[PDB]
Amino acid sequence: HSQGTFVQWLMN
Amino acid sequence: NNPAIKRIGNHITKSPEDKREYRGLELANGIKVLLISDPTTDKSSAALDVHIGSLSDPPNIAGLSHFLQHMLFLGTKKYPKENEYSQFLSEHAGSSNAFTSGEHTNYYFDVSHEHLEGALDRFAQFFLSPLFDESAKDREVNAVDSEHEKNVMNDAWRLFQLEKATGNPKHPFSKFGTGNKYTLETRPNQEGIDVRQELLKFHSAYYSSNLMAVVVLGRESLDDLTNLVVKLFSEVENKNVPLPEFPEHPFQEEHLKQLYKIVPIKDIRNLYVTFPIPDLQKYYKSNPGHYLGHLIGHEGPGSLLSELKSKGWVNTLVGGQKEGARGFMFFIINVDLTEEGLLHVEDIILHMFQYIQKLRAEGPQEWVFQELKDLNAVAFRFKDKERPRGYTSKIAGILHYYPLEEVLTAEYLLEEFRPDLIEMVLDKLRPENVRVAIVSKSFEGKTDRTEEWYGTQYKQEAIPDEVIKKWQNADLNGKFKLPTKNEFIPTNFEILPLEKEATPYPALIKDTAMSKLWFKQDDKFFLPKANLNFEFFSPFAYVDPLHSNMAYLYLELLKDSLNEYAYAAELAGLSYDLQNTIYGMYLSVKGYNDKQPILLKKIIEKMATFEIDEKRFEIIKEAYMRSLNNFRAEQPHQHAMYYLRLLMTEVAWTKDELKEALDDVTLPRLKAFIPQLLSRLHIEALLHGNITKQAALGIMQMVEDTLIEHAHTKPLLPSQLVRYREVQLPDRGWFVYQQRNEVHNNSGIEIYYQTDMQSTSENMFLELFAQIISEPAFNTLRTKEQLGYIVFSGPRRANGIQGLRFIIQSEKPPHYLESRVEAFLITMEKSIEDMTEEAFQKHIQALAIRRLDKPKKLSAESAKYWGEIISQQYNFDRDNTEVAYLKTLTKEDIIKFYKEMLAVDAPRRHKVSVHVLAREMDSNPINLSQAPALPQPEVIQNMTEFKRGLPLFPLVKPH
Ligand SMILES: Cc1cccc(-c2ccc([C@@H]3[C@@H](CO)N4CCCCN(S(=O)(=O)c5nccn5C)C[C@@H]34)cc2)c1C
């Protein structure tokens, strides 16, 4: 499993 | 010619299967713009990305950027109604949201294609004249505190911010990002800071047009879309803000060779190995981080994960490059830890550097790069059509990183084979650069430090130089071979011609005692893909808790067995999903159809001839026990939903019941379970995609013949195919189930107003009322009353029954939320009687647009059908049927529905509530609207007795 590139969201 | 446009982008390269139209622009003020013309789309969308984020937060006002994100929604100079934005979108089938990363703030919405401009005008005003109303500032700060409070007891967030607390404190990386009531109100009001000024000061300072990117997707022409964007957005002021950049890494020498022992909230055992690396973003065509992530993270034969798994030390491994801001990146390896692996962490890390050393000894491999290049190439050509909302949001983010013409392809296509960069990155993966983090409850009480923001308990140690040296002298391990040519890569992308007898909906092409095969050849997307869904029914998969535990462990062991083999197929865009259900087993195979039957057979053979490795059995069983126990640390509102599901379902085993019965699951008893489970079955399948009728019939027959041969499977009797019913609540009753959440210091609540069996009529009464209250319930219960961050309302559908439900997670006690939601309901009764006759039809067209939104990708269409099938209702034309009826509903019909079914004094009210108390909440008993007086609720003391004393609903007649 390779994972590439938490963030705080406004709404539920 | 045009002065508002600095330039226009030459053809924007796209997938030759992408029928949409694209144009790139850079406005005069420097806003990079991508316009997407899709005359098909039922919803238009737009998004804007500001290259500013948490890292630019003022040191004294942690979270200002995230708080400002919340605040743009609540009023503009031209549209000063606090919720004019939410209200306009809700009335036109729209939705919206935003997020804040360290370097970006991303705003996006979608709306009915006929109202892009109206939404876009209200939307653009966010970045021109936001009010930052002092009253809304004092209210919305609570939503931010609920959001953080939610995350305080979350193991992932704690590790996220623990890393920030672990590096250079002068570095912006260490900044608290979420923000809460302390940093956004208490501490500022303590330091004399006028926050509305700092919100205005920041917005005016950083929300410059030169740091903005916009994507707009609508039915309008590319030219019309260009004028629209120029009209609304060229007035954004360009302050020539220099883009923030962070060359110095957050981890310096004193932060390397460090080890951290961390206490988790859940019972988990994880090991994180990290290396600081330079920013690889610029190398997007060579992509060296992916090359190394692909090999190190590989799960096939000869891989690192394999040996770690074989030694009983690890179960899962994830590796690759982890993002940090512009100028610094990471490389992570993530393994979970078995009980043994916890004791052999030193060896596990050694084995890691042994594999890395192998990669150095073999050098860069052009064939590997070619394989990665070819897979991405195929992936992009046959990419699925995205939903407009997420598509504009993502493109809006990467406009900052790639040329206008490359924006669609940059993240997919590879160009340069760069063995130098592969060695450059690979050189930073060395024990002198390594940082190790261990997460185990076994550090309970042995920590000497506390992370201030989340409370995390941890201990910091320097890695002995004797140990660093062991890692540096890593021999070659003869168990680590590079992977081999991926034999699952697809070669046949031929779209089969559309057969004469093809249908627009799935056809029932087989109805035997063992199989019920639904089939539809794809007539919309024409990609070389297919979805193969199978539902296996056995009364022995859920007959009692012990058997549920074995149903689970059986498939978890089976998937574990195949993982090495199946991993290649996954990389090749051929994936499968396999899990136990309350009725048996569920198996879905999605991806490119070329190699699909090869994988499906290998699964069914493995199913029917499975041999259990005892060492795997004992390890998976142990992880499963922790998985059950770990449910005690889930969010309060999820507890609420969990309980209600237990309360209203005819048969349902609780986690505690499963957890207790799990000790009786011996290896012998499991070995006996499997052939019993397979002895009698009924299979209901949907085969949908790029396949012919006789290919499907052959797929289904092959699945059967394999089971029959190796498991001697006979059919089930039709009377055995019994679905579970939902408890029928009594007229005018109100029941309350109360429980505590021992982990989270918030409370949760679900309120379920059960209406009646699902019906074309009863379905739309609910859906329309839910539409009318959708936005107001959020605006009243969150934006105004600030009951919590999580406030949801909408239909609840289960076992053929339905009703209205509210879900809230708050600091206030549940019985308080009960009144406030009850008060809100009376607010709606007036709100409907006063609501204009046009506004009513406004909501109808809004629901209609949503219900008729055409699926954009095969997977989404297949889900529509699969819902009709597992629900035993088979209403494939449901959307046209139900929308048609919806339009004839009158404002009076909805009021009769409310007064009869929902109102506090309704004759046929059916209310059951789940109260999940906060960790420390004692056992619970102005300018706000009037809450009605509520009857005395009957308190469920025992769930089994509750169901015994109530009827059970029927089951919906099918078709
Ligand atoms: C003190 C110390 C020392 C060394 C490392 C750490 C550390 C750093 C970061 C993490 C993050 C945390 C959220 O930030 N988690 C999410 C759950 C697992 C997913 N992953 S990931 O798979 O590794 C990963 N994401 C992107 C690429 N990849 C490979 C990130 C991990 C966890 C631990 C710490 C805290």
Image (tube, rainbow, N blue to C red):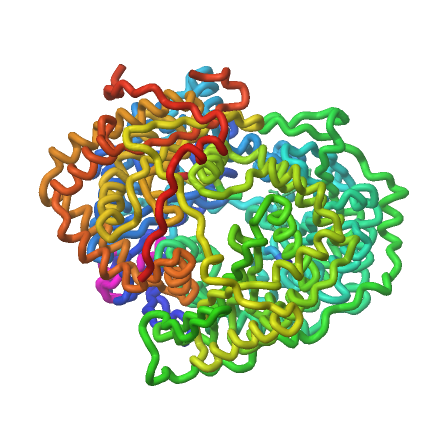
Looking at the rendering, the quadrant in which ligand 1 lies is: top right
Is there any visible trace of residue B310 in the rendered image? yes
Q: Where is residue B556, by image quadrant?
A: bottom right
Instruction: Tell me the quadrant of the picture where the C terminus of chain B can be found.
Output: bottom left
Image side of residue A9 versus residue B197, left or right: right
Q: Is residue B605 left or right of residue B508?
A: right
- The span shown in magenta is B214-228
Horizontal and vertical percent for residue B368? Answer: 67, 72
Position of residue B688 relative to residue B863, above or below, is below
Q: Position of residue B301 (x, y in %)?
A: 74, 67
Compared with B368, B184 (above or below) is above
Asked if residue B159 can be seen in this view, the reply is no
Q: Whole-percent x and y of residue B241? A: 42, 44
Residue B616 covered by magenta stretch: no
Lateral position of residue B337 relative to residue B394, left or right: right
Quarter of the view holding residue B155: top right
Q: Is residue B256 left or right of residue B193?
A: right
Q: State the residue at coordinates (44%, 31%).
A: B946
Q: Is residue B221 magenta?
A: yes
Residue nearest the observer in this picture, B275 or B505: B505
Q: Residue at x 12, y 40 (%)?
A: B892
The quadrant the N terminus of chain B occupies is: bottom left
Nearest to the observer: residue B369 or residue B50: B369
Vertically, is B828 above or below B231? Answer: above
Q: Position of residue B191 (x, y in %)?
A: 46, 17
**Residue at left offset 46%, top offset 15%:** B190
